[PDB]
Image (cartoon, rainbow over all chains, first blue to last red; front, top):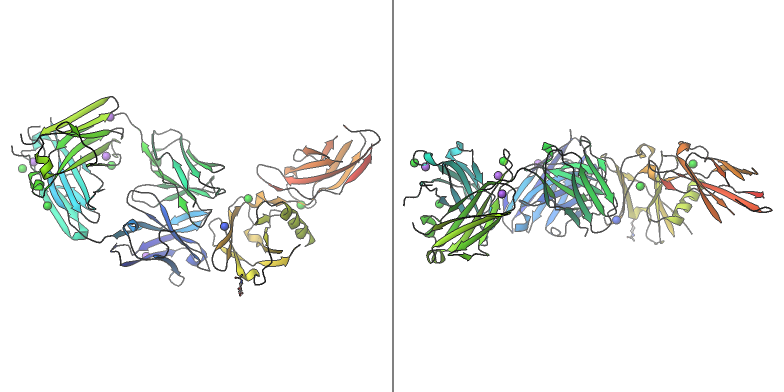
Amino acid sequence: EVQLVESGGGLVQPGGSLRLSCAASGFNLRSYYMHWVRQAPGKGLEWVASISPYYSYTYYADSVKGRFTISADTSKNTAYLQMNSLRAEDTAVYYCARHGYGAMDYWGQGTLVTVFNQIKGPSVFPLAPSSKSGGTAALGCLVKDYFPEPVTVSWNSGALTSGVHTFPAVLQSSGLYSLSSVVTVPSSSLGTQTYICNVNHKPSNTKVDKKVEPKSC
Amino acid sequence: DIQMTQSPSSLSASVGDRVTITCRASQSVSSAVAWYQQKPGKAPKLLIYSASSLYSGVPSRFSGSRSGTDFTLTISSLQPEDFATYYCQQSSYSLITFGQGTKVEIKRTVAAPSVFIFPPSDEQLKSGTASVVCLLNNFYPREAKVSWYVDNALQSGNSQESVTEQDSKDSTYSLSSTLTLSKADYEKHKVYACEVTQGTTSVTKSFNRGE
Amino acid sequence: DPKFESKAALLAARGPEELLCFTERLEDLVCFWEEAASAGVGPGNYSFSYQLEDEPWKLCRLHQAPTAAVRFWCSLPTADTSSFVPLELRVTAASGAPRYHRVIHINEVVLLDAPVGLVARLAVVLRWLPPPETPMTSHIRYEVDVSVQRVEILEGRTECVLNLRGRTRYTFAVRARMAEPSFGGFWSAWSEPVSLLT
Ligand SMILES: *[C@@H]1O[C@H](CO)[C@@H](O)[C@H](O)[C@H]1NC(C)=O
Ligand SMILES: [Cl-]
Ligand SMILES: [Cl-]
Ligand SMILES: [Cl-]
Ligand SMILES: [Cl-]
Ligand SMILES: [Cl-]
Ligand SMILES: [N+]
Ligand code: NA
Ligand code: NA
Ligand code: NA
Ligand code: NA
């Protein structure tokens, strides 16, 4: 019966603004403490803000004080997170959660806020197998220098999935992301079977399809 | 500002093991401590509140305990669905804080990686940078020392690693190590080597630029 | 009630916390605190709110009265005084700044009436009755005082066999408290004493 449904997350620049919504059902939102908690990619949970029942007292993490505003609209049974003065540390999945049993019993599904000042599509380079090799060859695609996250990678349009490893992206010293996607295949198929990595970077509306061939020597 | 120090940051265990996770508060939080379970792609799930009460629907193998500022989550007999990340939380102050989390990973037998080394492609060299990639495929445990040698000179500061989560079939890890050089530096040396060490074994895969 | 006031005075003398709560019969709860008298500060400058389990948070009307300072208190609706559940309490200033924050278990803050009907006789056997109108007497533990010498009594036991001196007047008194582990709380007042010339 109790449900929290979030919305509003998206790509935003610094000097832009965002408003996150958290629509509740199955309970009167004005009667509860409501919390916002965020989780940066690959990291733990960090509490962001709270609003108190009936009086709407607001409490904020130090790092968001003066830039984010939590509020609530009783008519729509919804809580909000208004976000201004955004920064790279603000990129995270933001959850809203209800207070119960001295803790957070019910949680929304999360909505992603991605902060960027530049958008750059990836360069894609082959990680070529050695045709001359054992019976198993590794090959892949290096997906370099894009921003922001994410990039998705499939092989042969999703027909090849067994043996694929697409690594988590790393933040390079340049400030741009980079990842590789690799797959292991039979050495004997290298002369006959085509291997194409399908790289999608929706922030830049860029799609790259790269056939990875054994290196001619 | 209350700190919730969770120990260990990760551990590996088997089905049926007894698992203990610890959370220490930097100051008194009374008993206002909760524990959450989180799985990839999902919201956290409340497991225990007031340090030791089980939330509804949580099976009885999960228990919590408090001694002073010391809080423990215990799973008496780990079950396959219990591998996840666990977080403690104090809500005794208005500034709510969380532990850094403890990932509970699947233990399995040791497994040596298949090691592959990739030179930079010719296309990338045109950009003025060279990325050399070393792949460690399907190994266990996660810890491995990956070192780069260029003409037998140990590299430092110019490589980055990425590692996958445990494979859902064989519980292994795969790892990439990427060495970044300028083109000018890449072209002035010959022998490129990735050396992988686990316990008492080292494996080095190399190539000679050209050839 | 002169009873609540005397029991509150007893608790206020000990603390240790500023925000103090006690139940009398596990179907009730009063929470109070004391502070210095401020000319512009009445109950309107504070909000008392609480949540039981995962129910909607509730507000409690604050009362105030002078003391030997000023005491604020709230009397919880009986419907919200269930045992063995987290009752989370908060006192918040009008600015929103938190003042007090406590989770309590009603079963752990019991302050009983004093034992009654103390009697002693030469075998010195000491007998008494539990506080009147009090359920779960089998869980009440006691302590007797000799006059300075304190003797602990196991729960449910209402008799003490007591070494002494001949030709001596001994004054005895007993007090009661709910016994661990399922219940807890604070010592009652001492009983009415009795004297025996040994
Ligand atoms: C208490 O509230 C009244 C309003 O009812 C206000 O005039 C007064 O200044 C407040 N006292 C303090 C100490 O803030
Ligand atoms: Cl490209
Ligand atoms: Cl081909
Ligand atoms: Cl997997
Ligand atoms: Cl308590
Ligand atoms: Cl009583
Ligand atoms: N407080
Ligand atoms: Na919404
Ligand atoms: Na091929
Ligand atoms: Na190994
Ligand atoms: Na893996």
